[PDB]
Length: 25
Image 1 (cartoon, rainbow, N blue to C red):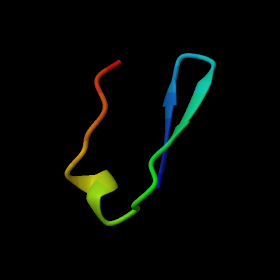
Image 2: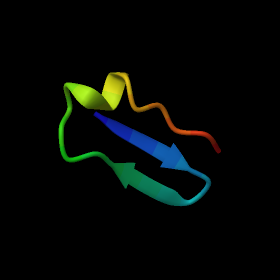
Image 3: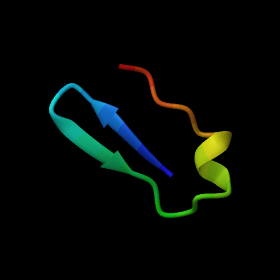
Image 4: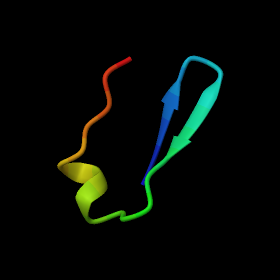
């Protein structure tokens, strides 16, 4: 459960919720 926002690696505390908490970059 990681995401990449440009050069920023984005991590979310709860991998479970990281699917519901989508990122918008």
